Image: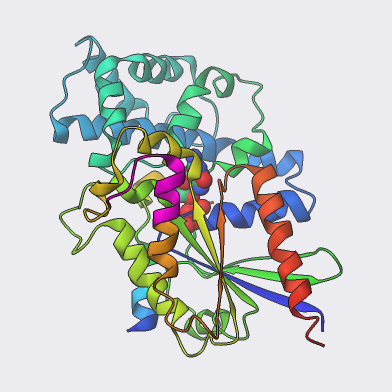
């Protein structure tokens, strides 16, 4: 059997579900126009959810609206919140969102997203409001990629590429159906650990004993060094590099690593993080890590990175 | 514990900003 088992791991919001969808676009035949239609309701809901999250955050952070006229829209949003659930973004609704998203109070809060929890499909959807507001609208494949869906168990995708049968599991965060879950961790060719680089500047939340980056690290530390994984490739996806590059211009990496004596260039910071992770590997003679810098929402990039990952797998099983 | 740590970690998404299918 030329069969390859790939397990995706990493904190929530690290890009795992996206990598899965992306395999479908790249190596299966994508999403058919019918399937795209099915995500219409999802796109609408996420857009609604995203703006609500910003609005609610305004209260907590105590940020006043740019124009106090928008207060009505805030109240109106909650009334209309369900207006799209099976159908259409009525015009009224588009108006509310459009006007809120434009407001400077909202925006100042959107800038301060490190201070709360704003999903990374927010900007994407809200800036394309005009396009998705159309009654005739059919979600593009880039739109389907950007959808945020609750799953309640193991996510799987399979494809054939370069004469190899690929099985990929995003095991997710649900223990229910426990034997099949544990099995995802068994007979794995390669583990692909995802990291959201852009988490580096997130405020230490009231429910955490260390920042998100160190949480990710601790996780990687235990995966990498687990004796069950001795003969499993460890592949590291330092993801969300697009957002990381923008943030690092303004927020110092010392926010995340106080001891960091380097500089706030994308290049130098990214290299520092990679080292922070790779240094966690405690069996360096018997194991190397395969680091990749990705933007998971970018098909072309994933295609290239995954192609590379495959080539290593091929060159690997030529120990026969 | 190895499996716990993973479970708890990957569960921490933003579920008020996702949706059922
Ligand atoms: N800008 C940007 N957004 C991303 C990137 N990777 C993922 N996202 C978005 O970030 C969020 C988390 O992605 P997801 O795959 O659902 O993470 P998971 O929680 O590990 O499954 C989603 O809104 C994605 O569409 C990236 O590299 N750049």
Which residue of the protein is positioned furthest toward the left in this rendering? Answer: A62
On the image, the x and y values in percent for residue A274 come to 45, 59
Which residue of the protein is positioned furthest toward the bottom in this rendering? Answer: A227
A266 falls in the magenta region: yes
Depicted A188 relative to depicted A10: above or below: below
On the image, the x and y values in percent for residue A187 come to 63, 86
Identify the residue at horizontal 42%, vertical 76% (top origin).
A175
Depicted B10 relative to depicted A249: above or below: below
A270 falls in the magenta region: yes
Identify the residue at horizontal 47%, vertical 64% (top origin).
A152
Identify the residue at horizontal 39%, vertical 55% (top origin).
A272
On the image, the x and y values in percent for residue A265 come to 40, 39
Nearest the viewer among B11 and A42 is B11
Residue range in magenta is A261-272
Residue A13 seen in the current view: no
Identify the residue at horizontal 82%, vertical 88% (top origin).
A320
Residue A67 seen in the current view: yes
Depicted A215 relative to depicted A65: above or below: below
Quarter of the image for residue A252 reads: top left
Nearest the viewer among A85 and A320 is A320
Depicted A279 relative to depicted A64: above or below: below
On the image, the x and y values in percent for residue A226 come to 45, 85
State the quadrant of the N terminus of chain A.
bottom right
In this image, A30 relative to A168: left or right?
Answer: right
Count of labels shown? Answer: 0
Coloring basis for residues? rainbow
């Amino acid at each position: 059997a030329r069969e390859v088992k790939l397990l995706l791991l990493g904190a929530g919001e690290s890009g795992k579900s996206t990598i899965v969808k992306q395999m479908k676009i790249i190596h299966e035949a994508g999403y058919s126009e019918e399937e795209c239609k099915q995500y219409k309701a999802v796109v609408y809901s996420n857009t609604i959810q995203s703006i609500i999250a910003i609005i609610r955050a305004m209260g907590r952070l105590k940020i006043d609206f740019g124009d106090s006229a928008r207060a009505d829209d805030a109240r109106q949003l909650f009334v209309l919140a369900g207006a799209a659930e099976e159908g259409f973004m009525t015009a009224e609704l588009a108006g509310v969102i459009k006007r809120l998203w434009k407001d400077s109070g909202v925006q100042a809060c959107f800038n301060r997203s490190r201070e709360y929890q704003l999903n990374d499909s927010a900007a994407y959807y809200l800036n394309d409001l005009d396009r998705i507001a159309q009654p005739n609208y059919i979600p593009t494949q880039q739109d389907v990629l950007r959808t945020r869906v609750k799953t309640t168990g193991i996510v799987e995708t399979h494809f054939t590429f370069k004469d190899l049968h690929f099985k990929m599991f995003d095991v997710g965060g649900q223990r229910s159906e426990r034997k099949k879950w544990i099995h995802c961790f068994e007979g794995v060719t390669a583990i692909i650990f995802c990291v959201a680089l852009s988490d580096y500047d997130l405020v230490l939340a009231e429910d955490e004993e260390m920042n998100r980056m160190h949480e990710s690290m601790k996780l990687f530390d235990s995966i990498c060094n687990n004796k069950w994984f001795t003969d499993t490739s460890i592949i590291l996806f330092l993801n969300k590099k697009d957002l990381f590059e923008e943030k690092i211009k303004k927020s110092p990496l010392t926010i995340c690593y106080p001891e960091y004596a380097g500089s706030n260039t994308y290049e130098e910071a990214a290299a520092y993080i990679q080292c922070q992770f790779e240094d966690l590997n405690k069996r360096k003679d018997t194991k190397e890590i395969y680091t990749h810098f990705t933007c998971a929402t970018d098909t072309k990039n994933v295609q290239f990175v995954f192609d590379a990952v495959t080539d290593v797998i091929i060159k690997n099983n030529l120990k026969d | 514990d190895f499996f716990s740590l993973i479970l708890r970690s990957q569960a921490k998404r933003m579920d008020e900003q996702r949706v059922l299918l």
